[PDB]
Length: 166
Ligand SMILES: Nc1nc2c(ncn2[C@@H]2O[C@H](COP(=O)(O)OP(=O)(O)O)[C@@H](O)[C@H]2O)c(=O)[nH]1
Ligand SMILES: [Mg+2]
Image (cartoon, rainbow, N blue to C red; front, side):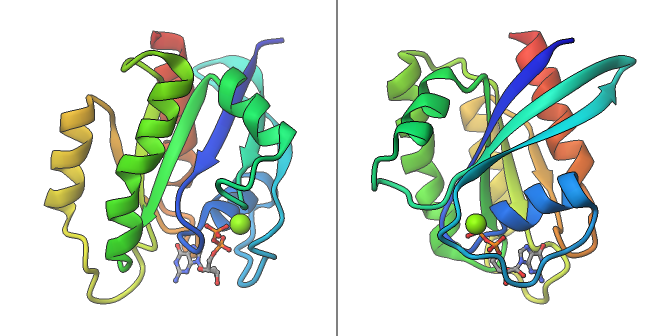
């Protein structure tokens, strides 16, 4: 049975754990320790292939743990998440994408740009800033809400599709 090794990256606070917990447990968690970094496993059928996702929900960025360095080096695809009401999280995407590029000595790494918290009012990052950035990197952009679950499956399934394509 095929396994897809996925890494969820992005600023503290943007919804990486909430998105992961939606996928795994189908509920929205309001507070999940922002310091917990761990891996989760989910068996799913995507385009008629029963597969296993092995997902690292990252937490303590730049404080090097041997589990993160390994998923960094061995991860096959990356969800790069910012929050649409957090300008700074969106500006930070560059740094994450740069860390991914450096570790893979490649600009062709399976990646999806995720704009989360779509359910929130008066976003500060316009859809157009997100589309232009994903167009520049050559990757899909998917808007999500961990709260309502909109886009959550589509983000992870599209990443799996990007791994296949690569
Ligand atoms: N309204 C709303 N809140 C969210 C969403 N995703 C996460 N959150 C909230 O934002 C906070 C940060 O989420 P969390 O998953 O801890 O962020 P992480 O540091 O990126 O793991 C938590 O209070 C979550 O309830 C979302 O899609 N919509
Ligand atoms: Mg977290």
